[PDB]
Each structure stands twice: as structure tokens, then as C-alpha cells.
Length: 147
Image 1 (tube, rainbow, N blue to C red):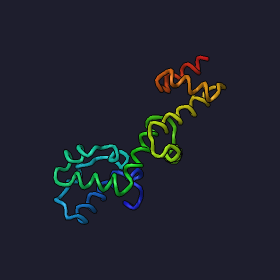
Image 2 (tube, rainbow, N blue to C red):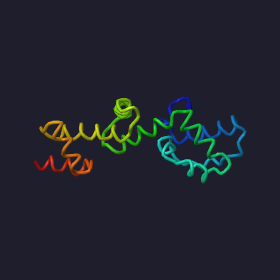
Image 3 (cartoon, rainbow, N blue to C red):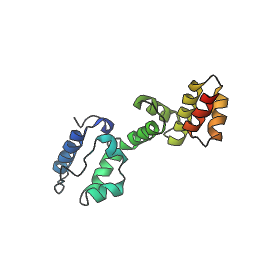
Image 4 (cartoon, one colour):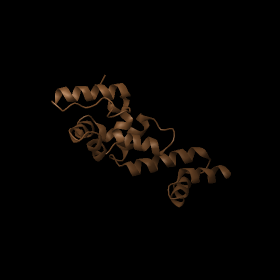
């Protein structure tokens, strides 16, 4: 199952990936309990976190995940989704494509879309309101609902 993108890996897939890596790269044994999480979580760990969890292999595992298996882009997709409620993997990926992988810009664009649908105001108004509220969508969304 590791052929799938890491964002879809289950916790069991993460454990299997570690077993595969230890075999493939002749790593020192990695305890199966080292990363008790799914692939989404794995993508959010920093290199320092990987080194802390695995002093012997953490940097290798991080590089493989982030810079070979597409973790870098998939982490950006997660950031976008976690920043804007109800965005799908596809929607986030598309938004990032539009900004050349710029997470801040993609998030702003999706916030404006979400606010725009909350009321009958123009897209230009939604942009002004969001910028006014320092891009706090929750605060902007409450103003719009209040009318």
C-alpha cells in the first residue's frame, strides 16, 4: 500500500513504510511504536522531530518522505485544508497550483471564496473585509452573518 501518496497512508501503512525503509536502507531497527500516527500526521513532523524519534534514521526518513515521496506538496495541501474549513485535497491542490505553491496566497484566495458565499456582497467587498480582520475568516464570517 505504500505506493499511495503519503497523505492517504494509514497508521498501519506508516509502520509498514518503516519496515520497508529499514530493509531497503539497512537501517538500525526502528521500533514499530516510533511513529504512532497516520500519514497526514507524519507529514507535519519537522526534521528535528524525526531525529528526536529516530536518532539513527530520522533525517533519512524525513528526506525520503518530504523530498522524494512528495511530502513537501502534500504538507502544503494539509496546511491549506487546516486553514480553511471544508476544503478538499483536490481543491487545496488546485489553489496551490494557481499560486505556484504559495501557501499564504492560496489560503487568502480560498478564504475570500468562502466568505463570498456566506453573503450577497461582492468579491471585492469580501477581500476588503478579510484584509480588515487580518484574514481571520471566523471574525469576517461573523460580521457578514450579522449583516
